[PDB]
Image 1 (cartoon, rainbow, N blue to C red):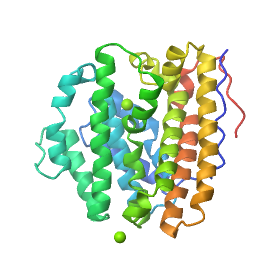
Image 2: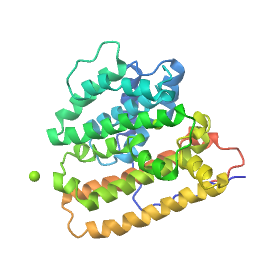
Image 3: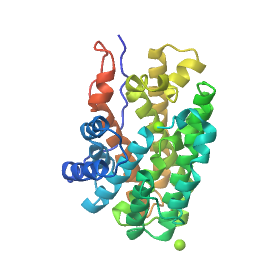
Image 4: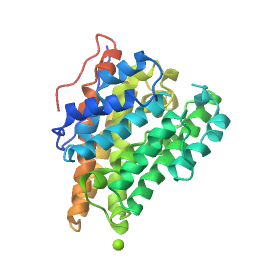
Length: 319
Ligand SMILES: [Mg+2]
Ligand SMILES: [Mg+2]
């Protein structure tokens, strides 16, 4: 039987007080968007409690901010899930991006037939209502990078390759859209990091470590579920097992070791940041901590993730 390694994390684990009410509001918004095809998928999303992830990763923000962030998570989950099999055609996916970039740049009104485009325009305008032009463009840049990164996944599927560790660790930071969520921490909190605060090497280093932790933790806990989706090709467990000739168990343990090394590096760099940080930088870094820890709590507690593992699988003690 397999044993799931613990993912120890000293960061506080909290949940927004508006979690259940906003989850319901946001799911209703997604169900009415027409972004999902089929009552079956709509019901799967409802049971997934995406608002729980939003509330655990943004536990301090006001109700209106949580609703905006929850709608954005629902857009991302829907976009990832959904058609023309463009996930296996790099050329076709690349050629399908310009119309979406036009909408993101505010250069074209979406067509009434374009569920993803209509919802993206709506979210851009709602973010613009509570964010400066510099904050809007910081988010827009992370979304463009996420969209371009989808072509890289399609490229791997097209030639049936499992990506190498180095290529995967770099690209996994942008394929998962986590940076698009980090870009809304100051916005959701009602504050604004200055350009030189945001781009300070210490803030970028902590942001990159948090983004690694979230991607690797998600890859490990979703692994059993992801085996039913393109043989979990885009998953650090598959990548390490394949390229380092490991057993599934030793691959799981190496992901947990990478997690522990990343946590140590985060604590080390945060001590250096604690010397100079302004209140907004300190709130942003606490935001990164809540995101990493809240994501673990959500993923550990997911019926769909836990259920996919074989019945004899051993889960670690609560850390
Ligand atoms: Mg994906
Ligand atoms: Mg300035």
